[PDB]
Length: 174
Length: 174
Image (cartoon, rainbow over the protein chains, first blue to last red):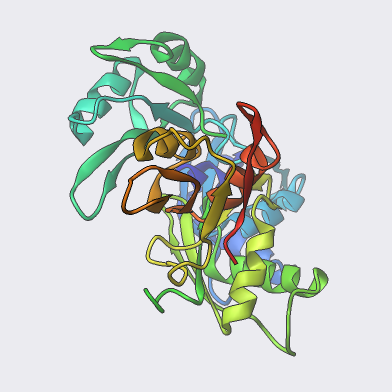
């Protein structure tokens, strides 16, 4: 989800011919050799490879273990020195591009509000706040966009928008 | 209640991804460092998290320690300011926070006097003391606020203040 990119690493300079399973076994082995796991089992859940551009992505079962694996930068695999880095969309500070949406008309439902937000692009997370004892909107919501670079384009567009009877507040929830 | 919800607090603005364990350790640690604990061992018994709406409820082992832990309202936890409140279900006992208002001009009626008090927030009780046979005010009133945290704000905003050629008195009724 949001934390998805806190559970992945980029791996460059991979050796010719190597398969996804062989990479998986190698990294699991190294994590156990160095005592870097936080529970029994295998930290790496999956591996995707681009053979043509000689790179792969690793996906881990946890955030703490993903961080630990960073210490393997420069490690040797079938003769070659691997390059380990964070994804370009890694969020050092999590939830920093989460938005608060305030001053919505109380009659508007989940999908209607979503439809206002998604004109700037797709969402990874969305919730509208309601009274559970009635089902009625309290008039605010929260969201995060798939592509965090769209965030500021959406604030510029929506903050202050006249929605019939009311004026929207749209800002980073912080 | 009247006696319900004595050992639970609402915690708003929790960081996403955080565990029930990590939140438990944090609050148990703070109670000790802050000197709020009243006995050996752990004041916090359990935590329940809604990951999607970023809030939790803590259950404490004792009534007084739940009360003490309200002083943490605003504390920073992994970059986020925590919002600590009583549950909506919690209500203090009848008249716990009754207020006396003296020095009102006696030509003023109930609604006129009530208007000054409801500027601070809504009332669950009010009575302007009147001479029964005639009907005209004695110049003092009693009231009680729905939100009991308003009580202290009313006092600070009205006590010792000028109203005509009279200075108001606003204090707890007992």
